[PDB]
Structure formats: C-alpha cells, structure tokens
Image (cartoon, rainbow over all chains, first blue to last red; front, side, top):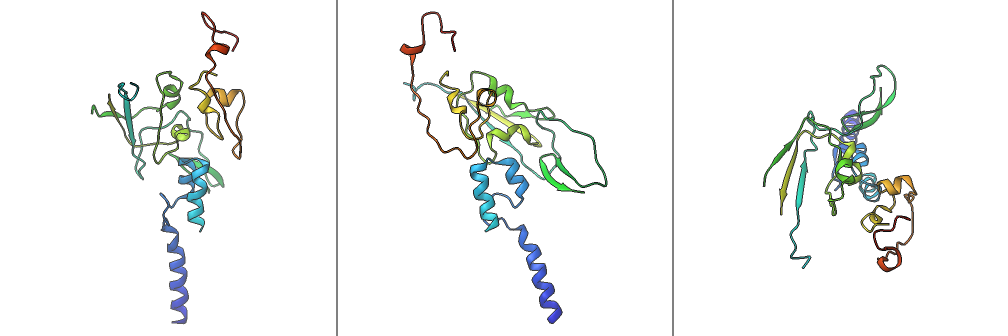
Length: 49
Length: 50
Length: 49
Length: 50
C-alpha cells in the first residue's frame, strides 16, 4: 500500500493535465495559436488555476 | 431603412479536427530538422521539441 | 444554402480582407487575425441574402 | 481616414494602415474619438491630399 498510494497519486497527477477546467481546449499552444491575447489570457488563466 | 435593407451574409464553417488537413494558409513549409531541439509548427500544432 | 466545399487550396483571407465589399466580421472559436495561420480539413461556405 | 478603416486601429489588430503607418501596442490603454468630416475634408471631385 505504501508503494501503491504514491504510484496512484503520481498517475492521477499525470492524468489531470487532460482536463479543460472550462477552457475550450487543454492545449496551450492551440489556445495561443487560435485566439487573441485578451481572451487567451483568461483561457490560460483558467487552465493555470 | 437600413434594418430593412438586404444583406449578403456568408457563414464559413471550419473543421478544427485532429485529422489530416487539406486547407492551409499563405505561409509555406521549411526544411526538416531531425535529432535536434527546435521549435516546430505542424499543421497549426505549435511547440518545442526534439 | 448553397453549401460550397472549399478544400485542397490555399485559403488567403487577406484577399477577402483587402476587398471593399467586406464590412462586418464576427468569428467564433478562431480569432479573425489568425485565420491565415491555421489548417483545416474541409471548409463549408453558406451564402444568403 | 475613410471611416471603415478606423476599426483597424486597435491593440494587435491587423490591417495595412495599422501595419504600415502606426501600430497600437498590445497593452494600450486609450480612447478613440471619431467623427464624420465631409464638410471639413471632402471637396468637389475628391480630396487627394490624404
């Protein structure tokens, strides 16, 4: 269990990057290459939060 | 009136998909760099990698 | 709606932008200043008065 | 300017006028006041001074 808890926590922390958190996409380069600054800096703000 | 005047309206719908693409912009392709860390732009997919 | 298939071609939106009969733009999901910097599979045009 | 070009003048917005004469910066905090000046600028058979 000591090994498995750390392995499961690291796997969960790795798999958490796929979530959008309300943004239109989970890819920062896609957001930056698709949108302007004034809304890119609130979509990336949501992703960073 | 201007609100009653006719308008030509065109809706353009694009397919931003994780798929092979046929329509691209005016900028063109450069030469390939292998086994070296560079910035890259593959069909709008931007990033930094080897 | 005459669904126009735009495919296998270079989309120059500066050609449409430089033309005089182009007054009101409103783009959703893609910033209109970056329409020349993306690639799409197929483009569908609909035109109506 | 001709009135349909003034909307180019914005932070980061493209266009020939805003690209080749003066660009507004991206962090620009400002105000834009425009008014039609036909009787002040437009003459008979055109005004070529602009």
